Image 1 (cartoon, rainbow, N blue to C red):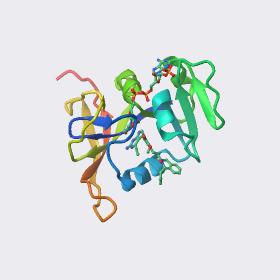
Image 2 (cartoon, rainbow, N blue to C red):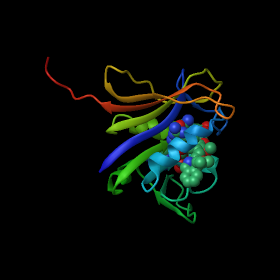
Image 3 (cartoon, rainbow, N blue to C red):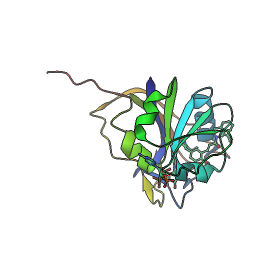
Image 4 (cartoon, protein in one colour):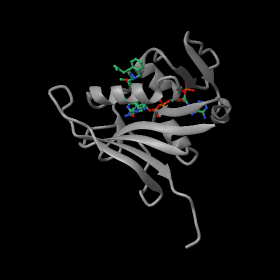
Length: 163
Ligand SMILES: NC(=O)c1ccc[n+]([C@@H]2O[C@H](COP(=O)([O-])OP(=O)(O)OC[C@H]3O[C@@H](n4cnc5c(N)ncnc54)[C@H](OP(=O)(O)O)[C@@H]3O)[C@@H](O)[C@H]2O)c1
Ligand SMILES: CCc1nc(N)nc(N)c1Cc1cc(/C=C/C(=O)N2N=Cc3ccccc3[C@@H]2C=C(C)C)c(OC)c(OC)c1
């Protein structure tokens, strides 16, 4: 009933490499935990295999065509259309295929911009700020543990109006 994208992508829109995050960034995991806590994560089968187990304290939903898929702690779905039946705040969690499928459908997007260029093999779909309003933009703090500049965006889809 309220559907969002949750993603971290670098300056070229890279989001993954060899089924892993290209970068080590603890604050963004804290970001993800705070945002989706008590809510619903919807993700594809490869993304789930990457994480390797349900995230606690929230509903984990996996989309796959495998009818044998039945993990403990994970609710499974078999079509995009199934996502609209999930109640509450749903976060499209990844990966590339689900982002491509969902980017025109979601209300808003919570994007962590990783301010670097990483080698990648999976990408977030292109988008333009002409379409998306910057609800907030906040620089992450850097320290010994979080050494890559990053920016937390909250983007809301702009309404189409006659001008
Ligand atoms: N930086 C970030 O914020 C971010 C977010 C999450 C993931 N990642 C990353 O994204 C990468 C992988 O992305 P990916 O696109 O290759 O895989 P993926 O999107 O995570 O999911 C792959 C799978 O989901 C399925 N699926 C997708 N649409 C479906 C539909 N309409 N009906 C039924 N099943 C459907 C299939 O499962 P089956 O083949 O089992 O049928 C499919 O092959 C990783 O390398 C990873 O680290 C990073
Ligand atoms: C972080 C990757 C990513 N980033 C963004 N912005 N959007 C996103 N949609 C994601 C998606 C994402 C995620 C993760 C990691 C999730 C995770 O490990 N947590 N998040 C929820 C959670 C809930 C309860 C307890 C612990 C956690 C834990 C956070 C810690 C404090 C350790 C991940 O594995 C490393 C991954 O690999 C492909 C992808």
